[PDB]
Image (spheres, rainbow, N blue to C red):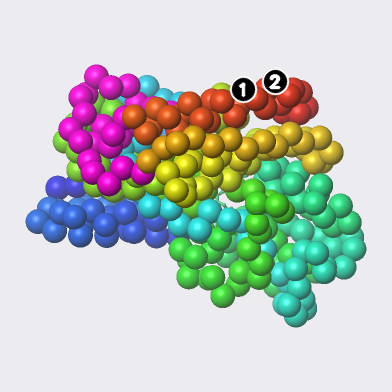
Amino acid sequence: VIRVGTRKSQLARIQTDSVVATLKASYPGLQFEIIAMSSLFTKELEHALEKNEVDLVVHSLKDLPTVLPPGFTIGAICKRENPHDAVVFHPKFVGKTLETLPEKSVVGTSSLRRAAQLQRKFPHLEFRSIRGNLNTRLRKLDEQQEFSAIILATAGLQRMGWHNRVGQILHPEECMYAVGQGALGVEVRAKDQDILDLVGVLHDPETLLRCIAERAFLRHLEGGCSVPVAVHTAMKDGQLYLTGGVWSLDGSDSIQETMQATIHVPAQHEDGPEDDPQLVGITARNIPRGPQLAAQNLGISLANLLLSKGAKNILDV
Ligand SMILES: *Cc1[nH]c(Cc2[nH]cc(CCC(=O)O)c2CC(=O)O)c(CCC(=O)O)c1CC(=O)O
């Protein structure tokens, strides 16, 4: 049996089921039991793992820290869903963008990354804090008299089935995404080789590499989930392009730079050794180590350039 622990929440459940459906397709001759428990929530799922009550936990990659706690690791980086930030609008706005929205219009977001970027880009728009989950945030926009629009993740809206509410997908010139956004991560016990082996199938090499680069960049910057650090990655013609940015809380101050590295997306897998340290919290012992190391190096390089341009001033408000 494969005991998968999940949060009782609707978005946590869907993401969990999606990973389980892939593992099921890879391992049809194995049992999968689902345990539902309800960073307060991250902690109790990690206590179950400790007890061996569950073997896997499925999380969003942006929610995980760059250094996981002792004895845990990210066994699988899944294929990436849309990483972009999207705008949902108030019904009264018949085909508008943030650009065409009236001046002093309120925009709901609890992300400093989004608010910082969007304040700089759309200075004539007010950004207030919105609280709750997608269904709550969507109800508040529709019913209440406060918000003209709300900023949310395309991946998240997509998973709930509510891509019909996406009004505008924001591009990197407007609002670059969070590190690991649109990617699911599978947490596992670091010394359970049998569980790490199974989860190895879920690793997508293109996403894994981009996600190491992004996590390496953030770890070097001393960033985390709730910090105004944003990134954009791509892999085209054997090149990994990493754009990273740092903003002040109001967007007034911002450093943004782009670097690239010759890194090839590996088609084939391997049987790497157990003593290979996990990179940026990730265990990809069945994926070539050459390309992973290069991705981390690229992330570090970009963090080092940003810090040389005083990126630590902007962050330490
Ligand atoms: C680190 C961080 N987490 C969240 C909330 C969140 N977690 C998962 C998603 C869905 C997309 C995905 O799987 O990547 C989301 C995003 C969402 O639509 O809320 C946030 C956003 C803060 C908030 O308003 O909830 C952040 C911070 C950040 O993204 O900058």
Q: Which residue is mark 1?
A: 304
Q: Which residue is mark 2?
A: 308
At horizontal 58% and vertical 56% (from top left) the residue drawn is 84
Against 162, is 27 above or below?
A: above
Against 73, is 211 above or below?
A: below
- Magenta segment's dominant SS is loop
Q: Is residue 40 visible?
A: no
Disc 2 marks which amino acid? Ser
Q: Is residue 156 left or right of residue 58?
A: right
Is the C-beta separation of discs 2 and 1 under 8 Å?
A: yes
Task: Reply yes or no: does residue 252 show up in magenta.
Answer: no
At horizontal 27% and vertical 46% (from top left) the residue drawn is 267
Residue 172 percent location from the top left of the image: 65, 51
At horizontal 74% and vertical 46% (from top left) the residue drawn is 117
Residue 218 percent location from the top left of the image: 56, 31
Q: Nearer the viewer, residue 253 or 24?
A: 253
Instruction: Label 2, secondary structure: give it.
Output: helix
Residue 72 numbered tag: none
Disc 1 marks which amino acid? Asn
Specify the segment rendered in magenta. Answer: 265-289
At horizontal 84% and vertical 38% (from top left) the residue drawn is 252
Q: Is residue 223 visible?
A: yes
